[PDB]
Every structure is written in C-alpha cells, then in structure tokens.
Image: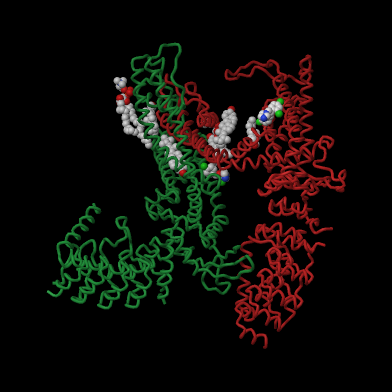
Chain colours: A green, B red
Amino acid sequence: DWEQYRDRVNMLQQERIRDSPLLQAAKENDLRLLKILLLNDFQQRGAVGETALHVAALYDNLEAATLLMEAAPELAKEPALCEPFVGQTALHIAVMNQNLNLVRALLARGASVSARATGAAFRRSPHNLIYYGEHPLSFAACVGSEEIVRLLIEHGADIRAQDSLGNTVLHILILQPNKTFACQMYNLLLSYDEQSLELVPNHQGLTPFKLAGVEGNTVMFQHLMQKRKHVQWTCGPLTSTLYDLTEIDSWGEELSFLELVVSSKKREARQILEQTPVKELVSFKWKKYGRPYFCVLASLYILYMICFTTCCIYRPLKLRDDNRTDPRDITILQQKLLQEAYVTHQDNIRLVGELVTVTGAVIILLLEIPDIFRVGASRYFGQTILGGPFHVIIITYASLVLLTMVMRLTNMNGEVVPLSFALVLGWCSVMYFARGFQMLGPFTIMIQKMIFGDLMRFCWLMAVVILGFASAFHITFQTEDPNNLGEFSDYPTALFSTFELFLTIIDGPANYSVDLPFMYCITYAAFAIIATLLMLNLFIAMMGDTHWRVAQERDELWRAQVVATTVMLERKMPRFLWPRSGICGYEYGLGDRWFLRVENHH
Amino acid sequence: DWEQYRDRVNMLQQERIRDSPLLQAAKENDLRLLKILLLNDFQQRGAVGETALHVAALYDNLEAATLLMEAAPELAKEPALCEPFVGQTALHIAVMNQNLNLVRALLARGASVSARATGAAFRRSPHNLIYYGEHPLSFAACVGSEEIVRLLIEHGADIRAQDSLGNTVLHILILQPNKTFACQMYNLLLSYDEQSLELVPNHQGLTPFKLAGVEGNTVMFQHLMQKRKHVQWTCGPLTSTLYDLTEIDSWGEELSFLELVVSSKKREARQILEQTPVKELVSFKWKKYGRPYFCVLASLYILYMICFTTCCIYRPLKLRDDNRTDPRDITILQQKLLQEAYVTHQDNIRLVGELVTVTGAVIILLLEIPDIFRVGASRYFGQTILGGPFHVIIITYASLVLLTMVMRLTNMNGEVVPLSFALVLGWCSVMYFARGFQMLGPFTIMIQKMIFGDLMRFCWLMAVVILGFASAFHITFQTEDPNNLGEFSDYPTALFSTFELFLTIIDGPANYSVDLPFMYCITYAAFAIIATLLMLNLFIAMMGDTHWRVAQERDELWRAQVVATTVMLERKMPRFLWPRSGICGYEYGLGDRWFLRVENHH
Ligand SMILES: CCCCC/C=C/C/C=C/CCCCCCCC(=O)O[C@H](COC(=O)CCCCCCCCCCCCCCC)COP(=O)([O-])OCC[N+](C)(C)C
Ligand SMILES: CCCCC/C=C/C/C=C/CCCCCCCC(=O)O[C@H](COC(=O)CCCCCCCCCCCCCCC)COP(=O)([O-])OCC[N+](C)(C)C
Ligand SMILES: CC(C)[C@@H](C)/C=C/[C@@H](C)[C@H]1CC[C@H]2C3=CC=C4C[C@@H](O)CC[C@]4(C)[C@H]3CC[C@]12C
Ligand SMILES: CC(C)[C@@H](C)/C=C/[C@@H](C)[C@H]1CC[C@H]2C3=CC=C4C[C@@H](O)CC[C@]4(C)[C@H]3CC[C@]12C
Ligand SMILES: CC(C)[C@@H](C)/C=C/[C@@H](C)[C@H]1CC[C@H]2C3=CC=C4C[C@@H](O)CC[C@]4(C)[C@H]3CC[C@]12C
Ligand SMILES: CC(C)[C@@H](C)/C=C/[C@@H](C)[C@H]1CC[C@H]2C3=CC=C4C[C@@H](O)CC[C@]4(C)[C@H]3CC[C@]12C
Ligand SMILES: Clc1ccc(CO[C@H](Cn2ccnc2)c2ccc(Cl)cc2Cl)cc1
Ligand SMILES: Clc1ccc(CO[C@H](Cn2ccnc2)c2ccc(Cl)cc2Cl)cc1
C-alpha cells in the first residue's frame, strides 16, 4: 500500500543522508566538516535523487546551503529524480520553509522559478496532507509568503502557469484551509493579472469562481463577489446593491455554477446556496417559477398514480378453470387472456388508462436515462440533494410497468408480482415531491436518514434474534399437532411469525384448550423481554437520540434540495416557461450583463 | 410583482442619473463640471421626478448640494413626483442621511418642514424595510438624531402631524426596532407636548400606549409606565408603588387595551402580559373572579354534555319493520317516528333533556355568532390565544344538534350521522376549559401544536404508504376466496385495513389453515418494516424532538390563554359579577382614577 511505500521512501532517504558524509553535513550544519569535504564530487544524491543542497534546504541550513552553492553553483538548478519527489528543486523546499534569505541566494544562482514538482508527493490526493500544486509561486502563495511571492514574480514566476490538474495559483488558493489569508494572497496575485486569470479553467473546466462554489469555500466566494457587485446608493440605514449574475446564473454554458454546487459531494458546498447574490436568486426562481411548476408536476404525477392504481383495481380476471382439490387452496380467480381481456366497454375504458400507464413509464425512462449519463450513475443514484433513491425507485417502477405490459401481451401468468412492486414503489415515489413543501420536505429527509442509519443497524441485530428464536420456536412445535398452533408449523412460517411477534403485529401464540410445550412459555418469555420490551423500545430511544442530532443537517439538506429542484426544473423544462432571471443590463445601458438588485438594512 | 417594479424603478433612476450630466455631477461631486453646468435648466429631473438636489442629498454631497442651491434656491422646495417617491424632498433625504449641515442649508433656503413623503416607498408594508411615516420630523426621530429633531421643531415641524395611517411621531417611534433609543427620543418629543400627544389616536383608534401593547414593544410599555406610577413610600428593602390603571383597564372604552394585546398577531404582544401594572392586574382578576366563574362554566358545560349524551343513549328506536334478507345485514332496530317517539313517561323525561340540549345549541350560537363579527372571522377562528379551533367545533356541534332537531321533526332517517359527529365534537370541546387549569392547560396546547404540526406532516406521507400498500394487498387477494381472509376483499376495506395495520390497531392477516399468496408475505414484511417499525416509531421520535423545543412557548401561550379567558369573561358576563378592579382614587382624594398598588422587595 502507498503508506508503506512512502514510509520506506522516508526511511531510505534518512539512511542515505546518514551514510553520505556530505548529505550528513548538509543536515547537521557542521561547517568545519562541510568546508573540508567541499575543499577536497558535489553531484552526490540521496535516496530520491535529491542533492546535498536539497538536504541543506530541507533542514533549513542557510550556511550549509550557501557553502554548497559557493562550491558548486549548478546545484541550485537541480531537481530531485525519483517517483515521489520528481522535479522538486532546492527552491521549492526553501519556499515551503519560508527562508527568504535562502530563496534569494538560490534565485541569484539561477534556480528555476518555473520548475514543476511533478512527483506524486505533490499531487492532489487523500494520500497527501497538503496540495500546493507544482510551482515555486504556487508554493509561496499557499504558504502565505507575500514577500516570497513578489520576489518570485519579479524573477519571472509565470502567474498563469498550470499544474497536472490544470489548476492555476488562484485555483490552488481556493483549495487551501486558511480561507482568510488566501484572500489577501488572491488580491496580491490579481495585482499582476493586468483573458483574465479569474477566467482560466482547470482540466475539469472549473474557473476559480466555479471551484470556490464546488469546494464550498464560502469565504473566497463572498470575497470574489465583493468585485462583482456595485453599490447603487445608501440612504440612512438602507443600501441598494446590484450583483452581476454572469458567473452564478451561467447562461447558455454547458454546465452551470448552480448545477456544480448542488451536485458537489463536499458538505461545505451547500453553504454557498446561503450567500447574498445566490440565496436571493434561488429564492426568486423558486417562488416565481419553481414551486408553481413543481405543484403542477406533483399533481399530474399523483393523478397518473391514481390512473395506474385504477388499472390494477379493475385488472382483468375470470373464474378458475379447474377445481380447488387441495383443501388449503383459496385461489378462485385467474387471469383473462389478451384475446378475452378486451371485450366490454369497461375494458376499452381501462385500455386508455393502461396506455396512459405505459406511456408514463416510457416517458419516465426517456426523462431519467439521459440524466444518469450526464450526472454520472453513482452521483445520480447516490446524492440525497439530487434525489438519488427516488431515481432508483422511479426507474424500477417504470421497468416493472413495462415488464407487466410484456407479460400481458405474451399471456404470461403472475402479473400480481410486478404490479405489487409497481404499486408500492410507484406510490412511495410520490415522496419525491415532498421536497417542494416546507411541511413534508425535512421530514422526508428524516425518513431517508432513519432508513439508511438506524433501521439498517436495527435490522442486522433483529435478524439474528429472529433466527435464534424462530428456530427455538419451530423445534419446540415440531413434535406437536399443527392444527392447534399454526404459527411455527414449518421454518418459513416460524421465521415470518417470529418477525411479526418481534414487532407485535400479531398476537403471541396461545390456545388455552390444549397443553402447549413448557419450553414454549420459557422461550416466548425470553423473546418478549429481548425482542418486544428491550429492542423494539430501544429502537424508539435510538431514533429519538438520532433525531435531535440530525435535525440541523436535515433542514440544510432540505433548503439545498429545493435549490436542486429549482436547478433541475430550469434545465429540463421548455425555456419559454423559465424567463431569464434578474435584470437585463442592456435596456439600462450596462451592456450584455444580467444583474440581481438587493436592498438591505444595516 | 412589486419587487420587479421597485427594481426597475431603481434601474431607471440610476440610468437617468448616468444620462443627465447635471445629475451625474450631483452624484460624483466633481465641482469643476458642476460649476460649468450651473454657469452655462436647473429643473432637470431623474426617473421619479427627483431633482439634481435630491441626487446630491442622496449621495450625501454637501458641496454639490450647496452649489445647486446657490445656483437655484427654489430646488430646496421641490418634491419628487412619481408613484414610489411622491412628495419626497431633498430635506427628507438629508435628514435620513443625518447631514445636519445640509439640513440647516436646506431649511435656510425654505425647504418645507411639513412636507409629506406620500409615495409607497414610505408606507408601512411588508415590501418596505423601514417605516418612518411621512414628515422630516418623524424621519429625524426614527433616525435617532436629536440635534436634527430640535432643529426641525424650531423651524416649525408640527409635532402633532399625522401620516396616511394617522400615526403621529410617537406612534412611529413605538414601531422602530431600536426600542432603547426610541425612549430618549420619545421624551425629547414629549418635552414639546405642552389633548396630550400621548392621547392622539391613529386611524385604527390606537393611542401610542395601546400601540406599544399591540406591537409588543415591552421596552416602550415599561418606559410609558414610569410616568403612570407613584412611589408611595420606601422602607428598608420594601417599596410601595401605585400604578394608574386608566390606560390598561380601559373602563367603558369600546375596545380595551387587554383585548387589543391578547388578540394581537405579534408574538411579542404576549410579553406585555408579564409587565408590573398588568401581571398583577390580570393575576388579581383571574384568582378573584376568573377561575371561580370558569370552574362554574366548565361544570355547567360538562353537565350539559352529560345531558346531551343521555339523550343519545336513550334515543328513540323500535324493531325493524322488514326482514334481514341479505345474510350480511346486521340492522335489527330503526328510528321511531315523531308521532310514536313521545308516548311513555321516560320519553317525556327525555324530551326535557332534548329541549335543554337544543336550548344549549341556540345559546351557543347566540353567544358565538356576534363575536365572529367583532374579532373578525379569521382572528376568531385562527388565534390560539382566543380559542380559535374550539370556536369552530362548538359552532359545528350546535349546528349538528339543530340539524338533528330538524331531522327528528321531519321524520328524516339517519340521525346517527349528525349525532356521532355531535358527540365527538361536543365532548372534545370540553378541552376548551383545560385552559383554566395549570395541569391540563399547557398540555392542551401540545395537543394543538402536534395536530397542526407533526400529525399533519405524518398523515401526508402515511397516506401515500397506505395507498401503495393497500393497492398491493388488494391485488394480491383479488384472485383468492374472500371468506378465508376478509381484510383486503375490496378497495375500501383494503384501505381501511391497511390504515389499521399501519397503526397496529388490528392484527396482521393470517390463516394458517390455508395457503395465502407468497406475494402477501413479501408485501406485509416490507409494510411492517416501513409503516410499523420505521414510521410509527419515527412519529414518537419527531414528537419527542418537537416537544422539548416547543415546551417554553407552550407555557407562554398558556399564561396568555388564561389572560384572554379573564378578558373574555369580564367582557361577556354581567357587570354585577365583575366589580371594577383595583383601588378607587375618589374615596382617597386622588380624583376619578383607579389604581393598582404593588409592594416589592429590592
Ligand atoms: C439490513 C438487514 C438484513 C438482514 C438479513 C437477514 C435476514 C433474516 C433471515 C434470513 C432469511 C433466511 C431464510 C431461510 C429460509 C429457510 C427455508 C427452508 O427451506 O427451510 C428448511 C431448510 O432450511 C433450514 O432448515 C434452515 C435454513 C438455514 C438457517 C436459516 C437461514 C440463515 C440465514 C442467515 C443469514 C445471515 C444472517 C447473519 C446475521 C444478520 C426447509 O423447509 P421446512 O422448514 O419446511 O423444513 C422441511 C424439512 N423438515 C420438515 C424436516 C423440517
Ligand atoms: C392531512 C392528511 C391528508 C391525507 C389525505 C389522503 C388520503 C388517504 C387516502 C385517500 C382516500 C382515497 C379513497 C379511495 C376510495 C376508492 C373506492 C372505490 O370506489 O374503489 C374502486 C374504484 O377506485 C379504484 O379502484 C381506485 C381509486 C383511485 C385510487 C385511490 C384513491 C387515490 C386518492 C389520492 C389522494 C391524494 C394523495 C396524495 C398524497 C397524499 C371501486 O370499488 P372496489 O374496490 O369495490 O372495486 C369495484 C370494482 N372491482 C371489483 C373490479 C375492483
Ligand atoms: C415487496 C416490496 C413491496 C418491497 C420490497 C418494497 C419496498 C418499499 C416499501 C421500500 C424500498 C425502499 C424504501 C425507501 C427508500 C428510500 C426512501 C427515501 C426517503 O427519503 C423517503 C422514503 C423512501 C422512499 C423509502 C420508502 C419505502 C421503500 C420504497
Ligand atoms: C428483521 C429484518 C432483517 C427483516 C428484513 C427480516 C425479514 C424476514 C424475517 C422476512 C422478510 C420476508 C419474509 C418471508 C417472505 C415470504 C415468505 C413466503 C411465505 O409463504 C412463507 C414465509 C416467508 C418465507 C417469509 C419468511 C420471513 C421473511 C424472510
Ligand atoms: C367523524 C368524526 C368523529 C371526526 C371527523 C371527528 C374529529 C375529531 C375527533 C377531531 C377533529 C379536530 C380535532 C381537534 C381539533 C383541535 C383541537 C385543539 C387542541 O388544542 C386540542 C385538541 C382538539 C380539540 C382536537 C380534538 C379532536 C378533534 C375535535
Ligand atoms: C393516513 C391519514 C391520511 C388518514 C387521515 C387516512 C385515512 C383513511 C385511510 C381512512 C379515513 C376514513 C376511512 C374510511 C371511511 C369509511 C369507509 C366506509 C367503509 O364501509 C369501508 C371503508 C371506508 C371507505 C374507509 C377507507 C379508509 C379511510 C378513507
Ligand atoms: Cl409524501 C407526499 C408528497 C407530496 C405531497 C403533495 O402534497 C400536496 C398538498 N400538500 C401537503 C402539504 N403541503 C402541500 C398535494 C396533494 C395532492 C395533490 Cl393532487 C397535489 C398536491 Cl401539490 C403529499 C405527500
Ligand atoms: Cl379536557 C378537560 C377539560 C376540563 C376539565 C375540567 O376538570 C375539572 C377538574 N380538574 C382537573 C384538573 N384540574 C381540575 C372538572 C372536572 C369535572 C367537573 Cl364536573 C368540573 C371540573 Cl372544573 C377536565 C378535562
């Protein structure tokens, strides 16, 4: 694994540094020994191809570093050579240690301002504790060393240079955790912008502005917006400001800023939706257009589920064509064949409801399947904010409807099976629309967070209790007459009875007209204590405990689900239903831009 | 919508200011350009009829404003002209910007101290972030600018002037959010009162004192009471104070201060009921008169419900007059007709209970219907503090009793229907009286806050689960013999069974003497996990979470419901039962006033 490899790399590196007297002296700064070694081979390299000057820079030894450079000035030009540290110069190290005196002394000797630390130890990854990109300028920037940043830009640091992710120094500052200084650095770098560096995309296509949204960097987002706003007037406690929406609303771009924020996997990204140009924009879009269209679509879907349900209630059945010879058989009706299922006026009235039913299942797949391939199947089905679990069950619903159509046409028996799944999944998919309503929306997120959290843990331990007790109850009744207590009469019935007895959805077996096994009363007392009293009530206790701790995040997830719904509706619906949002600049002489005006009290 | 209109107004305003070189110079303060333009048409107006001097005042440019006034002194007199800003002078703007030097310079040039900003941007509304009324003095006051307030009063600001709501500067200060400075301003304005300005009503009929109650301004209320109290004595740690009740008790006034506070829709208004002249007054009224009369009325209503119930238990029925030919029919009795329903001594004893029952339903409507028209139907039925939901069900109860009387008299069949509603609603309306008792009162507010909150959200998602599963269970059993498992034998029974199975109020279907469908055991396992375990227990978890967060407001709502009951009883009951409260001043030589004396430890 990578941790064991990095560890060896570090161990071999320290071993070489102890083995070589020149690298050893570069780490210890014993200028006596180092002068004698240099007066007496300067190319000597550690375990990763690093020079004695990289070693002096790593241990921050300016005296050893200047002796090494005075003896062999060419060392200032050298990269490290091996897979972890490829391209790392003594200048990258001196910059990361903030040694301005060593950085000057290296630049005075031709150390490259444009060198790229291409090795893995520099790549963005979960493996690496930092990500400064690849260049001395990007290091000095993320390190928060203006004096080094100016010194490098003077010496030719290309400010528009890009690393292996395509990230410029501006993209890299958006990724750093000192969000507050990163701003002062962001302004220092834009003081040399003179296409703007603000508009350069990385290889994901993200500009710095889109990256601050995607990464949830709310401090850099609100800092970037201070240069995309104009104060129209202030009068007493009131100010009117005009925000340029060109970045946030992303008109006619192939993937918008708000899509990138709502689909981001960072929990910090949802906080961007609470910021001033945005909250007001997504709130305007939702009241004016989003909620009216979502209430119409919710109503049409519920009427379509009533239509589908009615085609199940009036499903085509006839009297069985053979006798119930087994006294335990209760089936009295059978399917009509296709050639007899459409004969009466009521069958033709149903056929309209069935063709509407099938048409809705086709339309569901025509609307769903393309969005799997844009968003990505895992995000499509995994993301709570995008509706992931409802996209699974609506595709499953439409698939079970189309399977039921193929079964009808082919005279295949057993349409009850796909229709029973399609009725449960079809109606529970009406919970998709709960996200538009402040009453139902946050509660539907508790249902989801309780299903995947507490109900899953409960069902795993509930299963071993049911297997223990269903087996004990089955073998207790194995020897007794099945007609006197039917609940445990075979292992599948004993499992199902024990599951219903666990949840108290059926009454505990009892027949006072006969002597039940004494081992049953012992086993059922232990079961009612463990299953019913302790665990079924411990479920309520752990749900009540989960609920107060999740209640803040559920509201944030709901406020984000409303924005994701707003963004979905505007991307999918015909534009004539969704007029461009905000204020057109052109009819007021402001040029091609579109704006949001907000008035605030202070 | 108004937001899009205000936004255009702001955009057209800024466009004109950029288009006109004179308004542009008034905003930028480039005295070079402005001197040349004025030396070279001074009437030029922006998008809302505002002058270049309004523009200089808005951008707070005293140098541009004094050049514009020096070139054309008549500009100081000008209002703005268009619908948002009608009547707004440069003096309104200079006052709101607190520019005392510009305000003098305008007043020195005849700017009107009595101008009214009649435009909508000044009206009280949810659309407007501030409300300063219409006059320069009311602006200077709400802005908290004594030096400008004195300067205006010297120049003739009519302190008794009223805006389009009838609000004086005192009413407007009660509405402002800096409740603490507003007091220092309130005293500054009363220093010029010399009918008192304290007693002038707005167009709602509210004086400043009633408005501080209605708006829940507890800081201004307790400040107003410092001038309506007298300290009789202090001895060591004890003080005795005498509060004038003339304002709070509002004797013989058509609508009292305490009615206006308990019927207010502001959540802050209930906090007035916790203040020193009041809490002691409403507590005295409740112990001495309120609770004794409310316990008598509670007892009389419960005895009337026992009387009505007894007329239902002894309802007049006879043997059916035709055979039960359908083997699934269980009806054996039928109504007696009016001409046979009153024959025995026990029928005449009932008839007294029925005439008492009907008389109580008439009395309920005679007591209820007038109060709908005073309070207003929406407040009458909407307000928790006034008893809103109990006023709905008591009017509904009386209507179902009078309908049942019309049915009896007309020999109409089916009296079971209106009587079953009248028994449920009649007895649940006994919960109205829970508000008098500290044990039952706050709990009856949780019942209400759980019905309209958590039970509503639950019932919406519970309904789609019941529609999904009732349909799956119905079509699973559609083909099987109805006599072996009756629960899902038609769609209305399948809905009702699935509702009872959701809540575990009936046992899960099972008949071990026959092979049930395998799809039933699959569907019922999924149902018991989703309905019974997860959601029925998630109801308890979300109620437990709502309960601790609502528990403070429920106690405040209960303490306010007791005062609303006290105020109701005193307004409705015969005065001889409700002696005037407090201490008559006349028999101690204090004149016509009535007082509350409170003794306090400090
Ligand atoms: C997110 C939570 C997920 C939790 C997942 C857990 C699920 C709960 C239960 C598992 C379903 C097991 C279904 C067994 C059906 C047997 C039918 C049958 O064929 O029975 C028996 C055969 O087998 C048995 O004897 C026993 C089967 C093996 C033991 C039970 C299954 C264990 C499954 C373990 C799963 C992992 C659990 C780990 C901890 C969670 C035959 O039938 P018979 O009884 O008529 O005997 C006919 C013959 N005589 C009359 C002579 C008796
Ligand atoms: C604050 C919370 C408020 C929540 C409100 C929600 C309410 C829960 C349930 C709704 C009541 C529906 C009553 C249906 C009665 C049908 C009787 C009948 O006539 O059935 C059927 C006819 O209809 C049906 O087939 C299906 C009816 C349509 C679907 C069910 C109603 C959907 C209502 C949706 C409401 C909105 C929900 C949105 C999400 C909350 C006939 O009768 P049969 O079965 O004897 O068939 C006789 C004929 N064979 C023998 C051949 C079968
Ligand atoms: C035999 C059939 C009837 C069984 C398998 C059916 C399972 C249904 C009842 C289960 C399967 C997954 C469940 C499920 C998945 C996830 C979510 C998202 C959550 O935010 C709301 C509840 C909701 C929508 C629930 C509802 C109930 C579902 C849809
Ligand atoms: C406790 C958790 C883990 C939940 C999920 C466990 C469910 C188990 C107990 C349930 C789910 C589906 C049930 C089930 C499916 C269908 C049938 C066919 C029926 O003719 C006999 C019972 C039988 C065989 C039962 C046995 C018990 C099962 C397997
Ligand atoms: C068919 C009939 C019997 C059905 C419709 C009757 C409904 C009754 C049970 C329901 C309807 C509204 C409910 C209701 C409304 C509001 C309140 C106010 C609350 O502070 C206490 C409970 C209380 C008083 C409850 C009691 C139960 C009521 C009165
Ligand atoms: C889950 C929430 C939404 C609550 C309110 C839902 C209630 C539903 C399930 C209940 C309320 C009243 C019930 C109801 C009313 C009366 C009858 C007549 C009876 O002869 C057959 C059942 C039938 C038709 C049932 C069906 C199920 C209903 C409609
Ligand atoms: Cl789980 C679930 C999901 C969505 C709805 C949709 O609920 C709304 C009503 N509502 C309830 C609360 N706030 C709004 C609705 C019901 C019926 C029809 Cl036909 C249209 C609409 Cl818009 C109900 C349950
Ligand atoms: Cl929901 C409800 C509402 C009101 C009462 C009234 O309860 C009181 C008794 N009580 C109980 C607690 N504190 C006082 C009562 C009962 C019977 C009779 Cl006849 C008269 C009275 Cl005054 C009881 C339930």
Left or right relative to A429: residue A462: left
Q: Exactly how many numbered labels are in the figure?
A: 0
- The answer to whether residue A201 is above or below residue B580 is below
| Residue B347 position in % (x across, y down) | 77, 17
Quarter assignment of residue A13: bottom left
**In screen coordinates, is A240 left or right of A142?**
right
Question: Between B200 and B445, which is closer to the camera in this rendering?
Answer: B200
Relative to A368, B428 lies left or right: right
Q: Is residue A413 visible?
A: no
Q: Reply above or below: B487 against A281.
A: above
Side (left or right) of B468 relative to B120: left
**Rendered-image quadrant of the N terminus of chain B:** bottom right
Q: Outermost residue, front direction?
A: B236
Residue A298 place in picture, x, y as percent: 53, 47
**Visible in this render: residue B240?**
yes
Give the residue displayed 14% in from the left and 62% down from the top. Answer: A19
The quadrant of the picture showing ligand 3 is: top left
Instruction: Examine the image and state in which quarter residue A324 appears.
Output: top left
Image coordinates of residue B140 in percent, x first then y, are 70, 66
The percent coordinates of residue A85 (x first, y second) are 24, 63
Residue in the foreground of this view, choosing between B560 and B361 = B560
Q: Give the residue drawn at x 64%, y 67%.
A: A236
